[PDB]
Image 1 (spheres, rainbow over the protein chains, first blue to last red):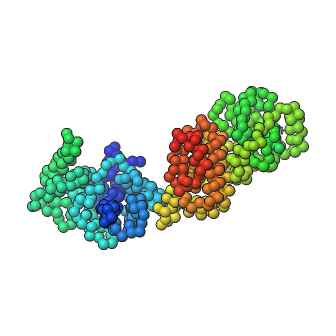
Image 2 (cartoon, chains in turn cyan, blue):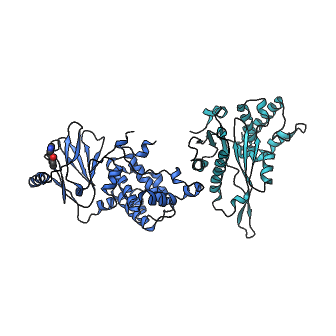
Image 3 (cartoon, chains in turn yellow, purple):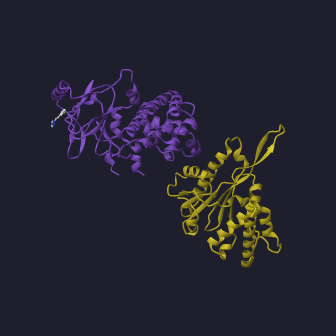
Length: 237
Length: 300
Ligand SMILES: O=C(Cn1cncn1)c1cccc(F)c1
């Protein structure tokens, strides 16, 4: 069934699973036309498919050409997501295919189930967690590759950098969601926090800065301060 | 006009015949039902006074043999049987008709209700859904489960309705996933109509039989099948015009006949609101939508 606070450690067991987030697949800017009407212009998007145990991110870039001549794009985006996830699974060796796919939005369940009818043994699950994966486009290197793409493209990342050398997957996922929650609540402040100190760099082959253990605690503390604050600034408390 | 005689009535029972019903008291001198119209299937059904659990009954067609009912005190129910000896049946019926110990099938001359509920129902198809090939008549009760219910446990006592599953490889062509899930016309027209049912009369007949089993026996899997077959049509963008017209008539008479007090369990809110207000055919069931809005505006 659904994924929630009670079965949270299931994410770090040895059964291959993937989170699929479709929130950045169909992206648009809304603008006025010369006649004073409103129109959308699509911009490139991405499917966020993540193995929470390993950190492996399968970033399928959704080029705006895929919407050309199509209607009901918000509905199509969910099916396009499911088609691309299904194609990903089929591309993987059998022993790498997931045993579960967890979608962050329930509207993805039927599209994915139908596209995965060939895989009756892969459980398609919703979740009750309010996961912040929509903020993946606040990670500069991810946004960069999506916006630069001129064609459909899959790019592989480890969203944990090298953290698993030093911490467990549970801790790595908690750090990831804290960072993403911060970036979602106040992107400027969150990015200020991550980069204020110019002596801490992001390795060419990483996404986040090369913080030491002690620096990560300071960082994590500042991200929680930000999140609690913005929650005050928002609710006046 | 045909007759289903009763050997006797040893237990108090409500007897149904098609949409009619009457009470028989324990050991009352009741010897059956006369004047049954020829040309239609019929259902004779039972609810014991002691045990309102298990409504049960028999689908039959009087053209297929001389059938009668006798109570079995070991199995505890009224059983339909066939009399092979024609002369003996004629004599037993005539004697009971002379002693006036039979109720008359009470059809009003204007009334096409039963025809309209059973227009496409054929005994040969009933006997394939209800498999018991040594009898010409078919037993159904409240508790029988469908083949599809068993896939999700006695195969001999099942309702072998056509399996319909919208999230199945049968329903969804590779590479048309979105197309075929949002518009079921492929599944309706090619897979079911052309492939399995052969024609829309056999489709409508199974739909009508499922409704009747749901209504007369409160058979839950029948109710699922009835709604599934409706939804498959309503969710198809491309349906023959004659099929929509006939479906609207079919549903209208089912909705008209349903007991007002059973709507809460026998009508699926989601399917009906989808079919009448969201689906491709939302504007194609005028008679059905009008009776539903005037009789069960609560469901909608
Ligand atoms: O066969 C029988 C009665 N019987 C014959 N053997 C044992 N019982 C029969 C046939 C016609 C109508 C009816 F009321 C009873």
